[PDB]
Image (cartoon, rainbow, N blue to C red):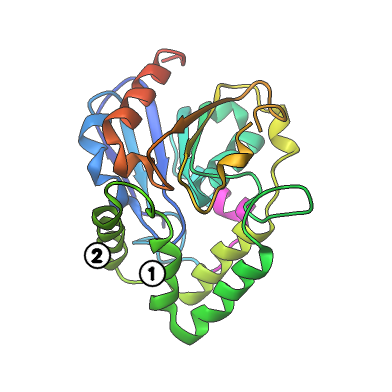
Amino acid sequence: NIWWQTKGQGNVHLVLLHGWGLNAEVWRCIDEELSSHFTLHLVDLPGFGRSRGFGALSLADMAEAVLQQAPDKAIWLGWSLGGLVASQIALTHPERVRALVTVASSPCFSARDEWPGIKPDVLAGFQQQLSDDQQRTVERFLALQTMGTETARQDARALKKTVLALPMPEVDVLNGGLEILKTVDLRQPLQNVSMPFLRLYGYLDGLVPRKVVPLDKLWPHSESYIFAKAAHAPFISHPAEFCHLLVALKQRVGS
């Protein structure tokens, strides 16, 4: 089944979804504070962490598996790949979503024609290298996430500790997750989401280039927030700022 921990007893539910290669233990830097304001749901995405009853999934199948165990209504927060899962839930079941919050996530992680992102051939490269050495490949993709910040080394250490605290995901899970990132393109459908839609970014993010942010035009109902001194993990580098933004959001949703 999916590994799912609930903490806190607040009137507003908040579901946190982690990024590729990680698990819900990445949230332990903010979970005490957030559980004082929310009923907090910490999830291992299907195939990751302790949710080991899955292989490769489509984004739609991943999101359906997550939704099965969720509360009726919640703020949905997704980091990186998690952001795509939350976005897919908001698109399919908007009545379950009080607000959509994406963190360091793109609607289309791959660079296309006139769209900034990661070269698809780069992701396809990582996919192949999983079968040579899955550890090293996961640690490479992961160590890209904190570069350039004042706390870069300590934050990378903290990520690595997360991945290493639980058994490694099977290689098909990892490969499937990279396939989601490489091919999914939610740019057009997220124009139609109507609940509060908050997009958080790190200025220094090497995976989601800050160029994409001024999505402000494509999605005029959405709102964006750039952490000046953060990379791809702003809740790790800037946890107090991050938590405060979620507390301010609570005011804008019903109970």
- The x, y position of residue 208, in whole percent, is 55, 48
Check if mark 1's residue and mark 2's residue have beta carbons within 8 Å.
no
Q: Which residue is mark 1?
A: 139
What is the crowding at mark 1: few (fewer than 14 residues within 10 Å), some, or many (at least 20)? some
Q: Which residue is at 64% across, 31% downward?
A: 214
The residue that appears at 66% across and 56% down in the rendered structure is 110
> Residue 132 versus residue 75: which sits nearer the camera?
132
In this view, 84 is above or below 53: above
- For badge 1, the amino acid type reads Glu
Q: Is residue 10 left or right of residue 227?
A: left
Which residue bears the numbered disc 2? 165
**Residue 49 marker:** none
Q: Secondary structure at mark 1?
A: helix
Residue 23 included in the magenta stretch of the image: no
Question: Quarter of the image containing the C terminus?
Answer: top left
**What residue appears at the point 60 percent right and 67 percent down from the top-left corner?**
123
Q: Which stretch is magenta?
A: 56-64
Q: Overall secondary structure of the magenta stretch?
A: helix
Q: In the image, 110: left or right of 13? A: right
Q: At 74% across and 54% down in the image, what residue appears?
A: 112
In the picture, residue 163 is in which quadrant? bottom left
Viewer-proximal residue among 2 and 25 = 25
Query: Looking at the image, is 6 positioned above or below residue 119?
Result: above
